[PDB]
Amino acid sequence: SPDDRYLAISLLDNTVKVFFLDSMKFYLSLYGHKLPVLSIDISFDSKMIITSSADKNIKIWGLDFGDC
Amino acid sequence: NKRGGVI
Amino acid sequence: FEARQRIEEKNKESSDYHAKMAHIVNTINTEEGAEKNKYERERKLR
Amino acid sequence: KSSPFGGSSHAKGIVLEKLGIESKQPNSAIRKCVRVQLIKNGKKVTAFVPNDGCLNFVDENDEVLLAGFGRKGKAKGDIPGVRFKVVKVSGVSLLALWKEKKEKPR
Amino acid sequence: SSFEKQQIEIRKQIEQLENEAVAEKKWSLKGEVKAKDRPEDALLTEELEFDRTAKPVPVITSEVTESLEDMIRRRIQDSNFDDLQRR
Amino acid sequence: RNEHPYMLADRFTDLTHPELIETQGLQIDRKVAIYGYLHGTPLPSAPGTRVHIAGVGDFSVAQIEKLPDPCPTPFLIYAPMSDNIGKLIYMDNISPEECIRRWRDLEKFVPYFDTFEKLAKKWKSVDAIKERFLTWYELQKAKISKQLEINNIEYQEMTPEQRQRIEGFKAGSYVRIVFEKVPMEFVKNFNPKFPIVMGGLLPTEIKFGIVKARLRRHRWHKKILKTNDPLVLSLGWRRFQTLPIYTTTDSRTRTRMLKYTPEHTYCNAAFYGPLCSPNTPFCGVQIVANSDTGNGFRIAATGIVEEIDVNIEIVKKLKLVGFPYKIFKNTAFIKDMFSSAMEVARFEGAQIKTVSGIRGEIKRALSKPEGHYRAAFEDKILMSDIVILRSWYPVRVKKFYNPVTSLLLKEKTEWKGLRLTGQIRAAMNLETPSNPDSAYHKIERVERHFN
Amino acid sequence: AKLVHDVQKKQHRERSQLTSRSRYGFLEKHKDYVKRAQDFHRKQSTLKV
Amino acid sequence: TMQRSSDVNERKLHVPMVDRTPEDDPPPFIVAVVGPPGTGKTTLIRSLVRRMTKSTLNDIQGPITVVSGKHRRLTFLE
Amino acid sequence: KYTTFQGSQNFRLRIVLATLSGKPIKIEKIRSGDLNPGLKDYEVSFLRLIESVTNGSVIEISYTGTTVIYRPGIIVGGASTHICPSSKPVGYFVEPMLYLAPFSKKKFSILFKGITASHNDAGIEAIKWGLMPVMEKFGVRECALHTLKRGSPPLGGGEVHLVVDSLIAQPITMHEIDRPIISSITGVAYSTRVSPSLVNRMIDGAKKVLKNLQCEVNITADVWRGENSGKSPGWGITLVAQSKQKGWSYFAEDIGDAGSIPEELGEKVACQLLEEISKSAAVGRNQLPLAIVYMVIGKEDIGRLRINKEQIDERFIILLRDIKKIFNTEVFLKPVDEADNEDMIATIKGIGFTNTSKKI
Ligand SMILES: Nc1nc2c(ncn2[C@@H]2O[C@H](COP(=O)(O)OP(=O)(O)OP(=O)(O)O)[C@@H](O)[C@H]2O)c(=O)[nH]1
Ligand SMILES: [Mg+2]
């Protein structure tokens, strides 16, 4: 995160784990692409990730609950 | 059917 | 407008009333006619 | 085994509530019915009171006396199931109440 | 006394509604009121109700025309309509 | 009498102050001790109970003091009027935090907890609560007797609550009561011949409202009972003259007003009055005095209370009758049931019927003959046929309520209230409001031919 | 009369024609109406045939 | 037989209610003397209290509480 | 001139006790020393709720909003709906009706709009599996509470529908003395309109702290799909200890707001459940006020009920003081005879009160 809140990690399992940097306590496992996510960005106040894969669609995800 | 009220 | 509203609520309450009381008379018909026929069944052999 | 309830011809029953208050058609077989608690068994059955005009004597928990009915035909509105008529309420005969000789005490 | 003024106000309402009872009826409690036995047009000011023969014409609203519009949207999207065929 | 705390009064004391009654000069509200013997349910020992004594109205108690009974028994005549934690809760001055701190916020529904981290340190192991985690007639008779014995057993406890402030003057104890606001005329005409009973009101019988009951003309009463015709009800404890109104659910669709009661069956009725429990019966009398007794039976109407509320709505029929003047085939022009274009514009679309029993519908206003308008029917109306518009005008009960208050009179009988309609008419020497066309006649059907 | 009284099944007298509208007398009731209407139906049916 | 018994044992059936009091201090049961006027009342009251306390009175009025037996009393009211 | 109160406290319970006893009430000084004083919006809506439920009840509010009068009337109920303000969820508006409810002329079908759950107030599975069973054992028979659609803070969109139609005369008198054995420990975990991983990692993270406990654990999952999810995303977890041998329940809750780990919230609710069963005996610390109101509003008997010592809090003191200054009923306290734990037993001579609204 740009305000070093937490880090998002993709997997080649079609998912992204949102994962704390202070605590690594596995905040979220947000998924739903069906072909591996291969770009991840985080909003400038750690509120909204933008995830994207080889399914040609980009998904804008609110971080308060991992919603879309 | 009602009689009361709030004032 | 008053005509349409009053005819609607009257049809709604009548369709409720018929089904509700026919429901209760049929359930109290069968849940005692069953044991009445079983009573005449057990009484017929004596 | 000698009767519809044990062996007795009559059994005191506690009236739960009047069945069929809200029937629109007067003198209808849903209207002239009432829930009654058999005491010597302790269970709830439903029973007739003839003449729904004199239904309104018996109201609620008034230890009525419960006799047999005996359908001697095939009446039209007559539902099956019930075979219990009410013969007294709280000690006094409700037939005598209907022809207004006696009085119901409370 | 307090009981005395109690009895005189009781006596007051006694008097007012005994003369109400013996006195003339309202027009609106007596049945069979013609036109000539009323206040002339008291009836708009009445809040009086009755029953009617048949449901009148449904006034066509924006919500009912858009409901049938989305109905025809669904139907002509799916092309599930019913025409005649040749022979 | 099994659900009401009642008491006959056998001894009476008008403990006012004589310098005070000489000071105001015969106007005071005489505070009175009533020395009596209570029966019924236990009397609630907190002073402030509504208690109705008969024939004056209901009061509230002010102080109550039980005495040793003057006519006791083996374990004899008596003729008066003749020859820690609990107090830590309930003491009022201190604050609940002081109560809990010397014993050791409720809009928030969840109970207050502490820091979750030390909670988890407490319940890392769970072994503390691990001990916790491992005929019908005589049936009801046994249940009620078991209730009575645990009642008496847990009444057998520490004295000052279960003997004078938590169970309340248990059953059958000679007590003294002090009322205030007793009017002077009770003491001024205190005849000891007439009894003075009293009974503690429930909370549900102090409020006034409208009671729906099911009446009956009493079977030895010689006269039918009119609507809006005053009679005195003996409902519960009170006796009051009120103005009943008799209704019938016409096939259980409505509650329409009658003019009298039926001759031999139960009919519904409504009246203003004090509230009471449902399923409670009452008698109801006509004229109670002794100047007007005759050889007539006095009890007028008996019956029980169906239910209660504060406002019922009852209607009555009224038939807007009209007259055709111009018929056609299957439609007609009708006249003077209405008077104005705005009236018929209100009543566009209403169903009507004829006295010949055929249906119809009032279609539209006629323009210039401002009363007259146009209606369509099943077939041809004759020129000699009155139309009918069934409608429901709502009537409402009158709020009249005199308790009889018999034992404040000068004479203690000859009580008067509202007289009956027939006798106020006879008193002001009027005549009954008859109607000449309303009277029936020996009708004469003639053999009507056809063309 | 099975379970009813004579005062339950007594009588209901019919009201007569008014005196205001008495020029065209004899208000006709439901039995008079059906007595007229079945005759009119008969005449219309034979006209149709 | 069972015939004369199985119909007469329903006299033991009722509505279950409660009677307000154990054997601690039952009250004087209120006994009322009602008749048409000019017969019975005061003389029957006098005779009953004379038998019940071996002592009559004169011009009795108001409710009078008189014992009757070692159990309980009662109360007379003309 | 009848019964008067100070302080903007305990307000729902004062109004429901006035409506039960039939006595009128003044309450003055509603947060008079405040920067924005007066009666709140949600409690004004609560009074309009009460006025829609009852009939003939009259209420005046101060123009300064710092006092409220209330003469009650009879309760009639009826099939209605109620929009609720977004300051306060539906548990706050359904909990006083949950014990005013079984006494009207008619049934109760009053469905509520708005937010389903919150932190401070009552969740809906909380209300169901922790306040239905105490009432079903007090004497009501058909009380039900369904969810048409859930909601979540702070956008809501939740629809909740209670019905009661066992209109009894009065509750029976409870006699519970022992320490009730727990027969099972169940619970449910719901998620409104987020991913379905949250529920399973709530359930396992909860049940890891009581897998060592011997008793049988059963937590049921429910996601909430589609339009029924409502208008805000959220999730929550409900734990209920069931005593089926006599039918009691304990319960503990939470919802998880933004920035909260579901594993940690699951074990947090399970540790608060352990907290409550430590502090509790035969009733929950939040099941307590409804229970003692029922035992004071039942029949003219002695109702006895056993509680452990830590139930007695400032809420208990203020509830007893309020119930005295409505209808002056002292509670006697029986210390149990085996007193290594000083367990009190509330015995109250109940009033012989009954509803007088029924069609009979
Ligand atoms: N013939 C006859 N007269 C009786 C009898 N008993 C009482 N009386 C008469 O009744 C008269 C009135 O006394 P009570 O009968 O006690 O009067 P009461 O019954 O109290 O009725 P009130 O005087 O109205 O209060 C007495 O003077 C007797 O003459 C009786 O048994 N036979
Ligand atoms: Mg005498």
Image (cartoon, grey):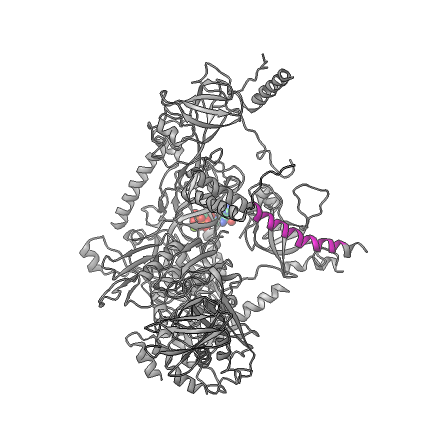
- Nearest to the observer: residue F61 or residue I307: I307
**Residue under the point 45% across and 28% down:** F362
Where D76 sits versus I12, above or below? above
Q: Is residue I19 above or below residue F157?
A: above
Taking the image as shown, residue F416 lies to the left or right of residue E71, namely left
Residue I69 in which image quadrant: bottom left
Q: Specify whether D27 is left or right of F78.
A: right
Name the magenta segment's main secondary structure: helix
Q: As drawn, is I180 to the left or to the right of I27? A: right
Query: In percent of the image, x 34 and y 31: which residue is there?
Result: E42
Instruction: Judge by depth and name the residue closer to the eye, F318 or C10.
Output: C10
- Asked if residue F198 lies in the magenta stretch, the reply is no
Residue closest to the eye, F351 or F239: F351
**Residue D86: percent from the left, percent from the top?**
63, 49
**Quadrant where the image shows the C terminus of chain F:** top right
Residue F368 makes an appearance in the image? yes
Question: x and y percent of residue I234 in the render?
Answer: 42, 68
Q: Which residues are magenta?
A: C18-40
**Residue most extreme to the left:** F23
Q: How far across and how far down the image is residue F403, in percent?
A: 36, 48
